[PDB]
Image (tube, coloured by chain):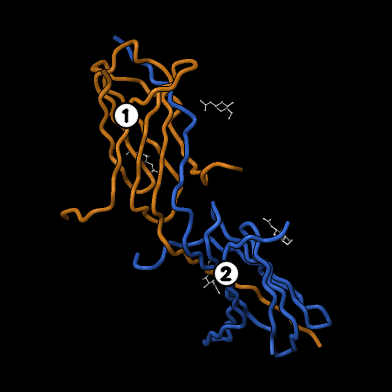
Chain colours: A orange, B blue
Amino acid sequence: YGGPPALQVTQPRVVLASMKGVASLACEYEFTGKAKEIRVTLIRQTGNEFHEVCASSFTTEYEPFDIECHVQPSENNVTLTLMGLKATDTGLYVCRVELMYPPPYYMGLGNGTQIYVVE
Amino acid sequence: YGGPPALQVTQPRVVLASMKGVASLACEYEFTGKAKEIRVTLIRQTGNEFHEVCASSFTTEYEPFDIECHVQPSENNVTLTLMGLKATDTGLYVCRVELMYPPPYYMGLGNGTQIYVVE
């Protein structure tokens, strides 16, 4: 149990690239609260070797109210748009989510326990 | 959405006190990683008013390897043992978990996406 606390990350099992060389892919992750920083990485698994295909970091800010990659975070969800794919880019792509500085305080209440006491 | 990030906390729906005035109650909570500090509170809901019945805080340390309350934390689980219950202590008891300073870094990997690209 040496590693970092795990994130449950889910990823479409298959995606078809358009004929234009564009693919979309959503990386969903289970987490409550917004961490101050997120980094998202797409790792290509070519057989035995792994190499980074894209990677974007984001921090929480005030906002008005070969393979190139667009990353759009969202509540528990990151859409990755790959462009400039060629035939040889076909293969397995693993999504990685990293969260840093989670909320510093969590709270929950239970639904209550009726305790019956008898003399 | 003003409040703290929520914890999912579950609580036995009913518990019978022993004839000796002792009841046990487990507060389970969903969380990955050990927060540096936990505080557990048992709140009695007598109709319209709420008052604290017990409350214990814990921090992560090195360890060798009317109503009074014993609290025993555990992985995602706190057992509360109430002693000295009387008949009038019968009623509704709500469990509250608070976590402070969660792990500062989380990571997960997805299962991979097969991207098919066609010329």
Where residue B64 appears, as percent x and y from the top left, is 71, 60
Crowding at dot 2, Cα within 10 Å, few <14 / some 14-19 / many 20+, comes out as some
Work out whether residue A62 or residue B23 is closer to the camera in this orientation and state it. A62
Q: In the image, is A73 to the left or to the right of B61?
A: left
Q: Where A31 sits versus B38, above or below?
A: above
Q: Chain of mark 2?
A: A
Residue assigned mark 1: A54
Of the two numbered discs 1 and 2 on the same chain, state the one appearing first in sequence: 1
The alpha-carbon separation of the residues under discs 1 and 2 comes to 44 Å
Instruction: Evaluate whether label 1 is on the same chain as label 2.
Output: yes
Where residue A104 appears, as percent x and y from the top left, is 42, 62
Q: Secondary structure at mark 2?
A: loop
Q: Identify the image quadrant of residue A54.
A: top left
Residue assigned mark 2: A111
Image quadrant for the N terminus of chain A?
top right
Residue under the point 40% across and 56% down: A33
Work out whether residue A27 or residue A112 is closer to the camera in this orientation and state it. A27
Residue under the point 57% across and 69% down: A111
Q: Chain of mark 1?
A: A
Q: In the image, is A34 to the left or to the right of A66?
A: right
Q: Identify the image quadrant of residue A81.
A: top left
Q: Where A54 sits versus B73, above or below?
A: above
Q: Amino acid at mark 1?
A: Cys
Crowding at dot 1, Cα within 10 Å, few <14 / some 14-19 / many 20+, comes out as some
Q: Secondary structure at mark 1?
A: strand
Q: Where B31 sits versus B118, above or below?
A: below
Image quadrant for the C terminus of chain A?
bottom right
Q: Amino acid at mark 2?
A: Asn
